[PDB]
Amino acid sequence: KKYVCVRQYDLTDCGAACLSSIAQYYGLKMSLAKIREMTGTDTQGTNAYGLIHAAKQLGFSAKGVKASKEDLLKDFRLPAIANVIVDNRLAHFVVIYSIKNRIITVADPGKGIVRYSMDDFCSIWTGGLVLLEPGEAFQKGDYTQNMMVKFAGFLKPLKKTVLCIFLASLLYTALGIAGSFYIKFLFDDLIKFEKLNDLHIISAGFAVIFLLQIFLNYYRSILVTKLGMSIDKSIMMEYYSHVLKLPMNFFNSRKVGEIISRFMDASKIRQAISGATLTIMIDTIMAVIGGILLYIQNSSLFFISFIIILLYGIIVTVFNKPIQNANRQIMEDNAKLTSALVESVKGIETIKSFGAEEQTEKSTRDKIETVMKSSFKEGMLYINLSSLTGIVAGLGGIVILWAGAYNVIKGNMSGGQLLAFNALLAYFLTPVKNLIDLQPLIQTAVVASNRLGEILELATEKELREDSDDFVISLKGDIEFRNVDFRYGLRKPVLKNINLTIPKGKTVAIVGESGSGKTTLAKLLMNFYSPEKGDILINGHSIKNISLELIRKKIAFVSQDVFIFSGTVKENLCLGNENVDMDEIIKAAKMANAHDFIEKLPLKYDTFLNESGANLSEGQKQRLAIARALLKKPDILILDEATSNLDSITENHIKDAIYGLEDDVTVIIIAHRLSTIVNCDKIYLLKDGEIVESGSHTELIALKGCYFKMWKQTE
Amino acid sequence: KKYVCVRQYDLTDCGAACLSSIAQYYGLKMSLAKIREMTGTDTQGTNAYGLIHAAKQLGFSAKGVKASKEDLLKDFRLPAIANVIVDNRLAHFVVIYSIKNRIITVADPGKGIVRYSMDDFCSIWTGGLVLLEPGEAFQKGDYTQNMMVKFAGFLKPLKKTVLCIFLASLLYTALGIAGSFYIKFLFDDLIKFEKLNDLHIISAGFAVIFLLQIFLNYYRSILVTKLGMSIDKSIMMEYYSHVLKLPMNFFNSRKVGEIISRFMDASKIRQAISGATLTIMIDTIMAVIGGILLYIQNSSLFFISFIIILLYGIIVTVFNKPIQNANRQIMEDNAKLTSALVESVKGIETIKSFGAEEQTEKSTRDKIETVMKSSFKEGMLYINLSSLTGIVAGLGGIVILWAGAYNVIKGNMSGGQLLAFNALLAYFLTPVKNLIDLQPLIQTAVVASNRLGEILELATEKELREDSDDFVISLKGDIEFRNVDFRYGLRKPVLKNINLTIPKGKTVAIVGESGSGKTTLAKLLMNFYSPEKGDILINGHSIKNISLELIRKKIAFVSQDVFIFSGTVKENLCLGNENVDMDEIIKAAKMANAHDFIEKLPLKYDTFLNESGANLSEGQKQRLAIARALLKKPDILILDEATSNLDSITENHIKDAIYGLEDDVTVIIIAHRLSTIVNCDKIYLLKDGEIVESGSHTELIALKGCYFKMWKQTE
Amino acid sequence: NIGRELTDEELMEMTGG
Amino acid sequence: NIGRELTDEELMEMTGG
Ligand SMILES: CCCCCCCC/C=C/CCCCCCCC(=O)O[C@@H](COC(=O)CCCCCCCCCCCCCCC)COP(=O)([O-])OCC[N+](C)(C)C
Ligand SMILES: CCCCCCCCCCCCCCCC(=O)OCCCOP(=O)(O)OCC[N+](C)(C)C
Ligand SMILES: Nc1ncnc2c1ncn2[C@@H]1O[C@H](COP(=O)(O)OP(=O)(O)O)[C@@H](O)[C@H]1O
Ligand SMILES: Nc1ncnc2c1ncn2[C@@H]1O[C@H](COP(=O)(O)OP(=O)(O)O)[C@@H](O)[C@H]1O
Ligand SMILES: [Mg+2]
Ligand SMILES: [Mg+2]
């Protein structure tokens, strides 16, 4: 078959792109976002294990192997995925499509289909190799939707506005074509016969025609601008409204820039949903009319103009791909340069301390040299294209004048007819030029449409939920963790056999080393992600059977990396609750040591916090998040190291406030320092993805084990 | 005098811009960066105390008062700085220039000289007011440099390239002017008299002329591209090399974006250093020759064309300012929208937990609507400008054809002469059009030149150093802190009266609460910043009397927030050390628990760390920083909370490696947890910018005080 | 004159970011 | 059938970021 090279949409889906390329080669085409989900792609890329798992899930019979140079000489199944080390810095995945004699053909998702010498490839190729092969169940499919047709459905509500633009454009074209004959009327009839009154009348008429043309252009431009803005708003709002409902495995498997950069894809789609269709509809008819009139004037000059436009189209089509390749290379070089500059400015402390101001300048100079070289290559491409186009256009114009003069001499036409032909050349050549120039626009728009609309196919969190029992209205009760496994994407498991029981209304504590997996437990309790095996039970009933809206309402979370949104203090403290009085916000502020703190701030509970509360320190944001947590009025309250960044008095006040919490409210505290929590009802110590000891402080100390050793070596 | 409004270069220098505006109004002009550094402007803006201090430094007599609504009616010193709350969200400084009849005129550095109804102003005006007045010593000055000449001095090495472009442009213009008579030769001579061989010969000659013109354009374009790239490289390298030498008060008083955004100012400067001067030199002569030739053809038609270009210039000049105002508003709205999107994506967990996916969507929709409104305003401005320009151009062309036909009828000229005039209209109108269109580019270039070149005037780290004594080559000795005060700019002081002595080579411990100021002393020992009062002495000799080089190699630092550069492990571990063998790196990797960690990494100490070592966790990077500091081979080594993120085994290994350190080297350990460091030779407990008691743990526990209370409460 | 003079602490509290 | 059949640890160590 053809060598399918699925270009990567992002910087980290090279493995997903390679797997998609293999699947499309073998006849299966699906969304790249879906495959990126199956491969377990994270913000740090994809490993071979994820590729193997996704291929087996897709019906392939995959395996991994390490190979040497002699293995390439041996024969095996050609379409395999291989590791490369670009610039001996960055690992990457490519697809080896064929191994010809001492040359290698690889689809690299970042570049395209390229050829490498065997020695150079073996130099840049790591021994890792993934072999893919269709299995028993590999039903070929086309599980994708034409995203251009889907996004063209936003023109249906605005059909009246598109109709007015089309009529205005037709009238504009007709008026311009009619007005292009002024030069013919001047020389053939007025100047030759010395008609003055007719000259004045005809000139006034053509001026009126031009004024009408200008008014039509003004109206059409207004309508086109409105149409484009409406389509842009619709696309961006749909994308954002869908993104806000996606599960948490979507957000932590993607960088912030990756999610945000889809907003420019909306403009890129709109540029073809509105611009391209309108351009096609108007310019096809305009070019047909212009060509018919040009042939009416003279056949030979029309053929010359057709040859001119054919040459222009040939040149532009030939120069299409190199220009876009150069632009992509420039973009990558600029990204590298700006990353280096940001790293150097951010880490100026270390540079100054180690006297590295000289080698840093050299590295930045080298990167700027690379950027300048890429810019010069692209500029040379543009200069060559412009020179060829100018040669074609100018020589064609001179040839048209020459042939027209010959025809006038021979009596085949008149001078005024030749001048009118020169005038109508605009209305014939500009439409065809625009139709040719739509080619780069459509490809970019299609890429952007795929990028933006592959996300809109992803199932939201509320759609993936099971049947929800409506009789469950309270989360107050025991919290049981059965045999529960977990892993972030397709990495090494974080939790292995987390089995525990939380009595209702009892303060409970979880302690452990950094990166042990306590925050993972806390997020599992809140339907953020789901356990691989087992279930989480609250008052007998399973979590999955509890309504998602309810459980997120009756569970409060105080993470370590608290986020303060740009808004007033009253708005930050009441994030989802839109019907709250003022006294209970005051009360919740008192128990979190924030009431006096915020009162000392200017104004009242109305101060907008600039740049995500940058003026507040870490402790102030900790207090605000805790206050919001109580304000939520939960049945379960999880405090993940909320007292680590606070001072002694504030920590003591928070501890005595949460300990003496009214109602049978379950409290869970995740701590790294053991001395911070000693009077807790029960303490859970998990070391290697499993609780190894459970009991009170008097019980855990008495029983020799990991807890006793940790207490002795930390206190 | 004229009301001076100095537009702010950054987003936080509004107070500095207001002070500069007052100074310029009163006759003193200087760089905005200098005033920004005397005002103590930071990443959070400027306070009134900074403005008062800087004004008194400049020679003013400043005073900060709070006034009521009635005090505006009472006559005071009109040029005063006032606080406003823009959008009721953000604080801002503006300049009140006169008290008029219920109308207030204010220079806002972000907008311009605007007028407000007294009701609107008093609604947004906060009680804050700053009064400025020259003192006894306010000698007016102009301590600023013309930054356009400074960056135009980069054209001196490339005088040959500029000269070749001028000659190529002259020949291109001459060939085009000569070729614009083909249509005159056709109609007047060849077509009229039916000359065929002469037709072919003349047409071939004009085709050859056009080909020569194309070749000249190709060569000139290559030269212009090369010149622009060279100037870009020169300016960017100059700026970056100077920035890397500036002191630390520059780096932490600015955001990374503020420092990096000056790199586009280099391109903005180049667009006028190369583009504008070459355009002026070529187009002035080309327009002069074209106008002379047009007047040769016919006076009346030349006058009509002059009127056309005059009207076009008038329209463009009129529409200049509103377009740039709309563009600035669009940029502000887009910045707000993208900041909101980034904040919403980053803090998705909180939004999902609190069920705020509905109001977040509404807020983003409102911001998108605001952006769409700004875009429509700018599009309407551009549409009106294009309509007016098209009216002028088309009616001018029609009027020129009309008057030319009238003149041909009257016998003042021929049809070929009229067509030649229409052809030369390009070579007359395009130069003047380009000269008029240079206006937006030159203003932007001037602003960018000021922004970039005001930093190149700042004194570097070395230039501010006192003369170095060459007799000191060893930093080994006692470290004495005299009565040392410190403050980050013009904020509340951090250190007050810390007098202490560190013996020669003895391990020393500093403990305290967060925000106490320990890292401040750690940086003051390294000549990052300087004490406000007192001195820091090493072996009797003052630090300021020792070469800045010897401080940075003989003192090693391990900050709490370690920074990793994108490079190999060997490169990271040896930042400034250009000559180190492998065995020293190996040994340094031993005591920092790095050999075991990096051995399990792929390959060896050659792995490139992607995105500032994002692969490695916090502890691994901290161990890498420990290894680098040990490899530095220092006489003084500072560990600012380095072991906080480490585990028990790693902490123990670090402790027994540091305690058993060879050579007479001093070790300083800055910690928050007292139990981490108890066996130190001496411990210093500083709470409020000063030490309250110093001694060993056996001595601090016995003496009741702050340390005993902290030990009892934490343990 | 013309207003109530702020002290140093009130001056630094008058943030103008 | 071309090389050593890597194990799970080496598979996850086969980073392709
Ligand atoms: C509103 C803007 C400014 C207007 C203020 C002032 C305007 C007034 C003028 C302005 C410029 C003057 C140039 C020509 C006039 C010279 C003197 C003259 O009248 O005699 C010439 C008239 O020849 C003509 O017929 C030209 C007609 C005048 C131009 C028409 C409008 C002006 C420009 C519009 C631009 C539109 C672009 C913008 C569209 C929106 C010579 O004619 P002749 O044939 O040699 O004489 C007989 C010869 N014989 C003896 C052999 C028989
Ligand atoms: C990168 C490449 C750049 C090349 C740029 C060239 C521009 C291309 C356009 C020229 C192609 C036209 C060449 C043909 C010339 C020609 O052929 O000129 C037509 C006029 C001849 O007259 P004719 O058509 O026969 O009319 C009838 C006459 N009669 C004998 C019946 C009386
Ligand atoms: N967003 C994430 N993506 C991938 N892996 C993660 C993510 N967050 C945590 N992990 C991994 O899960 C493990 C559990 O860490 P965590 O529970 O966050 O530590 P702590 O319990 O101290 O908060 C860590 O070893 C970490 O490598
Ligand atoms: N980069 C900075 N710019 C302005 N002020 C700072 C900066 N860093 C610290 N400060 C101020 O100086 C004080 C000293 O804090 P610091 O010494 O960093 O805390 P710690 O002693 O816990 O390391 C803090 O109260 C803080 O407000
Ligand atoms: Mg945690
Ligand atoms: Mg610190």
Image (cartoon, coloured by chain):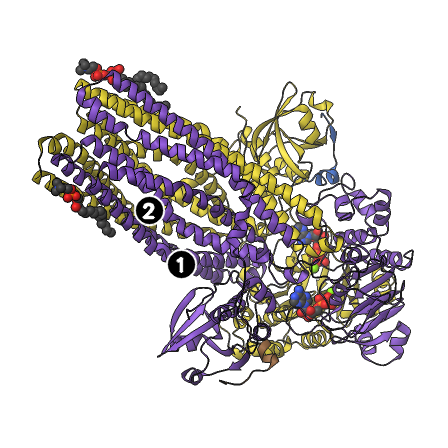
Chain colours: A purple, B yellow, C blue, D brown
Horizontal relation, residue B596 to residue B269: left or right = right
Q: Does B159 appear above or below B286? A: below
Q: What residue lies at 64% left-to-right and 50% top-to-bottom?
A: A241
- Identity, as a three-letter code, of the amino acid under mark 1: Asn
Camera-near label (1 vs 2) is: 1
The one of B490 and A295 positioned closer to us in this rendering: A295
Regarding mark 2 in the picture, which secondary structure is present there? helix
- Identity, as a three-letter code, of the amino acid under mark 2: Lys
Residue that lies at the very extreme toward the top in this rendered image: A197
Residue A349, percent from left and from top = 59, 59
Q: Does A47 appear above or below B61? A: below
Instruction: Work out how far the residue at label 1 is from the one at label 2, CA to CA, in angstroms.
Output: 35 Å
Residue A663, percent from left and from top = 92, 56
Q: Pointer 1: what residue?
A: A325
Regarding mark 1 in the picture, which secondary structure is present there? helix
Horizontal relation, residue A138 to residue A88: left or right = right
Q: What residue lies at 88% left-to-right and 62% top-to-bottom?
A: B704
Residue B387, percent from left and from top = 42, 30
Q: Pointer 2: what residue?
A: B156
Residue A531 can be seen, yes or no: yes
For disc 2, the chain is B
Horizontal relation, residue A399 to residue B707: left or right = left
